[PDB]
Amino acid sequence: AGSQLDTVRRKENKNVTALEACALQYYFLILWRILGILPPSKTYINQLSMNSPEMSECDILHTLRWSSRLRISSYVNWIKDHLIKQGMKAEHASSLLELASTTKCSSVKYDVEIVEEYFARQISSFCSIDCTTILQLHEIPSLQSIYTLDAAISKVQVSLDEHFSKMASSEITKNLLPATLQLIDTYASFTRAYLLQNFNEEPSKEKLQGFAAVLAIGSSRCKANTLGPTLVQNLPSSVQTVCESWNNINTNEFPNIGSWRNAFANDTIPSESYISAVQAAHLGTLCSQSLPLAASLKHTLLSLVRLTGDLIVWSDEMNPPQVIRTLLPLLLESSTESVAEISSNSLERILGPAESDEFLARVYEKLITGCYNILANHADPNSGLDESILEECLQYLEKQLESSQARKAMEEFFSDSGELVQIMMATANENLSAKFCNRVLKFFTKLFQLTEKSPNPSLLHLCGSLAQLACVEPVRLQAWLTRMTTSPPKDSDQLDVIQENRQLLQLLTTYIVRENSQVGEGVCAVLLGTLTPMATEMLANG
Image 1 (tube, one colour):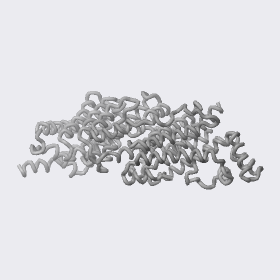
Image 2: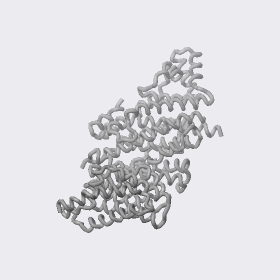
Image 3: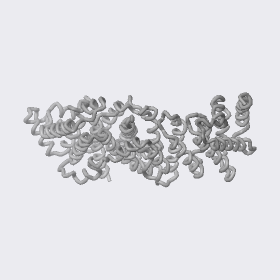
């Protein structure tokens, strides 16, 4: 009851009033007590023994509650005596209770599999969800699914901890890792969707994706990124304030690690009380009018990453690089910065120390990929990205050239995708400032010079990359050459900067024509031929 009210009022772009939020909390807290004091009925004990239905109609939690109860005999007794009163045959009762008890490791498995199936359900429901694309603010799940999934983790986790300490299963975690892994990435998109779409219009999906890419590149956790935070600040003050409000929100309301370990002031099974406190914190976020749904997503995602790290601890069947890929953006992003610390821990686990090459290798590679994405797929002003961002990382890109390790990482990506060419091809965009042209020219200038001052294969490979420039759109290349040479004082009041652009283009041509250059002869001719019409025009129009 009242589970889709938030989905509805948020669908109508309306904040659930405190009265309504409070009512939802009041209602859930009451029915939860009632379900708890009322003895489990025969049909439902049979279900706990059969479970043919997927319990889609809000029965997943109740089940865990009663299983935890049954684990304890007092409850076994209480429930079995109620079944005798209920009118169920006494021996039937005994058998059911024994079957529901799943004594031995079967109890741990019973828990594992139920949470596994809830995971599966959630994943499948996510089929409409796009992992690498911006999700509509309606694709975000209701707090119901958020807290239910959060409660599901709150259980598998504790149960497995217990099992492992007792052991002091591999296949049990072998199935949990993949299921959890997908959810994290999916909920990561939900956190972004809740933050991105929240941007105040006073925003175009083009602008929305621009802001998304910028805040992703932005990383303020673990290693001190000197580019992501800068671009995050560069974001419009409005967008910047939205991001600040998102980060201001925390998961402190929800009980943290160790609370159930402290028995949560609860006898028998304290995990049930921990899950109840988690639901109470979810309802408290609902009362708050500040990003309530994802405040819960922020916690659910944290719990998911915690469970993921737990699973990584054991071999399972996890694919090390794949798990690294999932935790990589989680660390390098402002929307999922909540788990950025836990993702860094996961990387220390699989990549190694935060100063280990692998770790740094992934960090910087992803960083370049993002910068590049902003340089080529966010150059258009429609992305709503100020020119400051592109030029800011353009300097960081040169900084990476200086770092031999980062230079090699950039070299591999740039040489394989001809990204260097794309940078000049992007420069063709007339919307980009003449300063962008100037900046681009230095970058390549310093690529060629650094090669001359200190020759190495990475630099040889970027010149092999510029050989791909030989094969570019002739019109686009000319359009780019035109922007570089033609000096209109109407738009470019800084003709001196236009002249610096001309000089740096001359320098790059001289570098490519050098015998030891790896750009090859084809590129030189390509440029030469394209300039011929330009020259002719400089004589035709005088």
